């Protein structure tokens, strides 16, 4: 019924945020989005995000370095999405697409230049003003 997904705005030395794009596979190029994933049973939201970032990007993050920013809340035909967004400017590893996905570091004021899922878009506005 209610799906909880956590996401992260990873910030580099130059105030670029990382967006990722699923591979084109057998059809067309997908949308740009914040890295993240489902919050699973027996995991805190922070644990889930930390694991997602390590699985997807080989980026290593400490819970004390994840800061709540905002959340999105979005109705779909068959479930409700609640999506907490964290920011993180202190992490270890070099982001690489470990699941064959595409990576793009984008200056914060430029994020709304890129096609993004409808749910991710209010989150972009919050990032610009912070
Ligand atoms: Mg994942």
Image: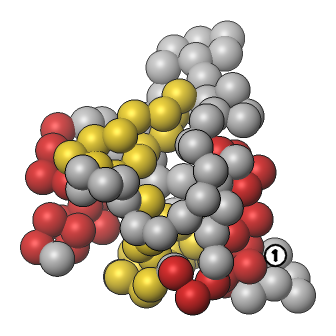
Disc 1 on helix, strand or loop?
loop
Is residue 79 in sight in this rendering?
A: no
Q: Identify which residue is drawn at 41% across, 48% down.
A: 18
Residue situated in front as seen by the camera: 3 or 99: 99
Q: Identify which residue is drawn at 65% across, 45% down.
A: 57
Image quadrant holding the C terminus, namely bottom left
Residue situated in front as seen by the camera: 17 or 42: 17
14 relative to 86 in the view: left or right: left
Residue 55 percent coordinates (x, y)? 76, 51
Residue at the far right in the pictured view: 42
Residue 109 percent coordinates (x, y)? 12, 52
Q: Identify which residue is drawn at 17% across, 38% down.
A: 113
Quadrant of residue 36 within the rendered picture: bottom right
Q: Is residue 45 above or below residue 118?
A: below
Q: Is residue 27 above or below residue 57?
A: above
Colouring: secondary structure
Is residue 127 in sight in this rendering?
A: yes
Q: Is residue 36 above or below residue 41?
A: above
Circle 1 crowding by C-alpha within 10 Å: few under 14, some 14–19, many from 20? few
Image quadrant holding the N terminus, namely bottom right
Q: Is residue 46 above or below residue 56?
A: below
Q: Which residue is mark 1?
A: 40
Residue at the far top in the pictured view: 26
Residue situated in front as seen by the camera: 46 or 95: 95
Residue 107 percent coordinates (x, y)? 21, 46
Q: Identify which residue is drawn at 43% across, 86% down.
A: 68
């Amino acid at each position: 019924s209610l799906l909880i997904v956590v996401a992260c705005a990873l910030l580099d030395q130059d105030n670029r945020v990382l967006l990722t794009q699923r591979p084109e596979g057998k059809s067309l190029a997908g949308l740009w989005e914040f890295p993240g994933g489902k919050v699973e049973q027996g995991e805190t939201p922070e644990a889930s995000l930390i694991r997602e970032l390590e699985e997807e990007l080989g980026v290593h993050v400490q819970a004390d370095n994840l800061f709540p920013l905002t959340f999105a809340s979005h109705g779909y035909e068959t479930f409700h999405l609640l999506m907490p967004l964290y920011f993180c400017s202190h992490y270890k590893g070099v982001a690489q697409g470990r699941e064959g996905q595409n990576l793009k570091w984008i200056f914060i004021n430029d994020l709304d230049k890129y096609p993004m899922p409808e749910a991710d878009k209010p989150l972009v506005q919050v990032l610009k003003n912070f």
